[PDB]
Length: 579
DNA sequence: CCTGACTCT
DNA sequence: ATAAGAGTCAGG
Ligand SMILES: Cc1cn([C@H]2CC[C@@H](COP(=O)(O)OP(=O)(O)OP(=O)(O)O)O2)c(=O)[nH]c1=O
Ligand SMILES: [Mg+2]
Image (cartoon, rainbow, N blue to C red):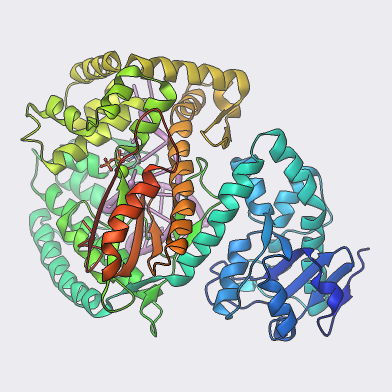
């Protein structure tokens, strides 16, 4: 049905100043991945181009990098990064259908053009999986079949842009797309392609020493159990703990006895073996994931790892990080924290600079709930995580250990996001009565927060969705469910999503503002990672003084709230030192 | 292939 | 039944 030219060479009419553009990368991980085909749809017609041809054509390369030639795409970051690996700069992306779909409804989980097309009853395009196949069968089809698919995807983007933009505008999300998510996409592309350098010699030595330690811990566990078994098997472990050793069963799941960390910690008064097992499972994860798993994805010639920041995945507007995940590198225990010594600057005489928003979601909550006491506290520049810790453990601001503040931080966020007396009791291993009391007092100190949380649940029931500061939405169709469990989970999403999502809006805006400030001040410094409310950069050592002023300022000023935003920062020779 | 571990925000 | 949002891995 759909006519298109299977071109042998680039022509002028393919180089119009507005086009839908498909630069096709089949591999899920697009770093240094093949570009298999290109499609262009514009006012002059529909074109398929072979990448060997087009990417070596100086005019097409020129067009790609010409910011005044506007392109509409789906997942422009994937294309931009794949092109960077081919030594080509992509500019002028003015519409991204993936990001537009994501903003309209994140629950749709849109991850191909066909799925976004479904949102407007557009059915003249196939899903990628149908065309390429799955798993071991995944392959690029015969050229005519490939060309039609890419053209159909380009035609879809061409026809769907206006309908999607119209609906975003109706929702007050058009700027959220064009001014926030789309510019962020190009920044994330830069960060991913840059990568982070790894000290493989240090990491390999850590791994050798870890293997030795695991063996020792392992044997000690076998001695304590009176038996060899697979400690990494919750099934086998459950038999040892609850049948052989006859320890109390505190919890079961659908598969059998729970051996969760929470459960094992509570069993410590019964048998010392549970502490050893908890240590073993920590060590085993360090080895499998942060030594072996990490070394697996290091590019050997540059020693860099290149994460992918998924910008259209989370239901709240956060990013996630995959292959590897660099947003869950250990920090809480010194043993694991040492992994961060293996993440180093990519040039000699450069340093790692890390900045972190202080009490971020509590500040956002203060602004949104308009809780006068919480607002007062932050205008007063107080630390609410520390105050809660003194309350919980009997101590004062002097005797608050970093571990103390950590445990208290979990209690603060637990309570505002709706933890029960049961959950708080199980968490601090205190009586349910004491836990209930603590929650009651908390909401007495911050009654605006309590009111806000009651009101936001009711609003969500009336409207069917909640919204963030920059107009991001999450729909919650389950929130009027007659079923208690289903309804209760949805109510808690109403309590959390606006706060976590507004905090995401803020750091996203901060990243955009920060790059504009780095370019104008012509600094060599550049972003490496985002970790939800943290930005990690690397820079020549000479730029540290300028960053110490620049970075906190830009982050604190990204939005203006009813309370101040506050950023902490550190720098050093490795990520570990940036503390 | 899922579940239940450990990891972070 | 019992704070929220994420990813990876070994075992099965
Ligand atoms: C740890 C944790 C965190 N969160 C959310 C809510 C906060 C943000 C930021 O994490 P951070 O530890 O920096 O918190 P922040 O308040 O910014 O603390 P700092 O002042 O930076 O220490 O993540 C949560 O919901 N539940 C948790 O158990
Ligand atoms: Mg923080």
